[PDB]
Image (cartoon, rainbow, N blue to C red):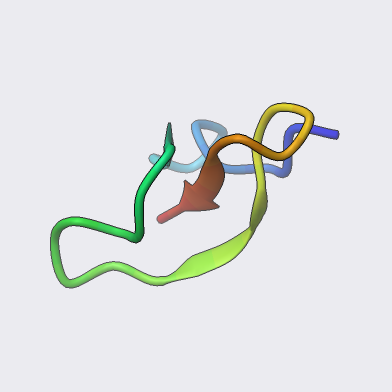
Length: 36
């Protein structure tokens, strides 16, 4: 289940978090991780 990412200001990326963010959970089925 898409974790509350974009809600506050996050995005899903197939690879590890880009900027100095931190991945909390997973976005889609599990191909992308939710970061914020």
